[PDB]
Length: 99
Image (tube, helix red, strand yellow):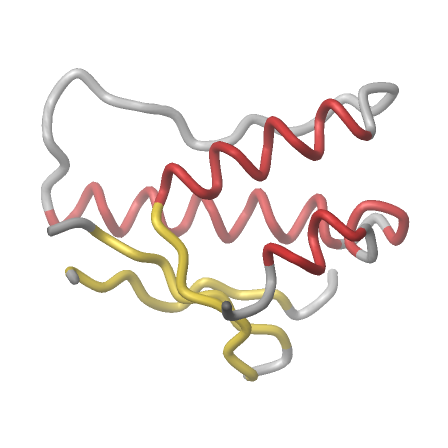
């Protein structure tokens, strides 16, 4: 429900995912940083049944599969950020920022 989006991935050598809230860019993060985010959030909020973070694959990802991972990360964030205590947590607010 909250207007969190991941409208792009970018090759930079690895891939980053560009996260926006209400059309404002908040951060640019690689997949492993999302994986760490999920582990941190789940430990902090373990009484919640978290949605599945998009997973790893036994092969390198094509352009189409990077787009699918982007969509999956957006769907994940749409769910967890729409829960106030999780979306406003120190963990999430740190994640959604630039160094």
